Image 1 (cartoon, one colour):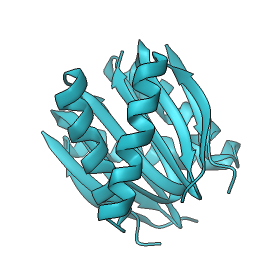
Image 2 (cartoon, one colour):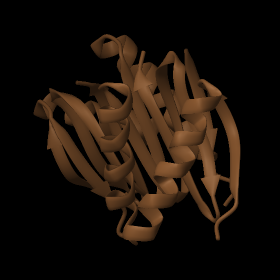
Image 3 (cartoon, rainbow over the protein chains, first blue to last red):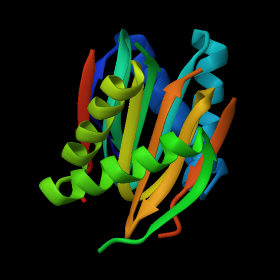
Length: 87
Length: 87
Length: 9
Length: 9
């Protein structure tokens, strides 16, 4: 069972928890990073309104501009997940 | 000198070329992926108006929603670069 | 539009 | 706001 480590968040605690749950579901169902990212993005578009963006991977850096209170960057096990709405 | 391979683009040829030039400049100046991404994002915010987002790395998948004609995904050498405006 | 990207490595 | 992320690996 994969360890969640939230690295940077500008997001309600309830939503941070959902992101972690959603990513857990995604990793259960899918093995390919883009499919994992697509599942998370789509769940959040639904649960929390569009428009979300998701990057999933083991090696990347980013510079994104996000809407306040709609950004999370976390690890689920060995995989890093960036999920946010654009600012 | 690093080989540019554009993998997916919804973007004018002039802008695709600028993205490749910008990423080339970034890789000359910086070694860390987030710094490379920040340099590209900032150049495009300036040259082509906000709001851009940039991910740079060797291992990641993504699902993002972009504005039509403002998306490029390419490699510069071994590094993958995702650059886009949000749709 | 929404699109996926996936690194080769 | 704009922020950076960088993977540990």
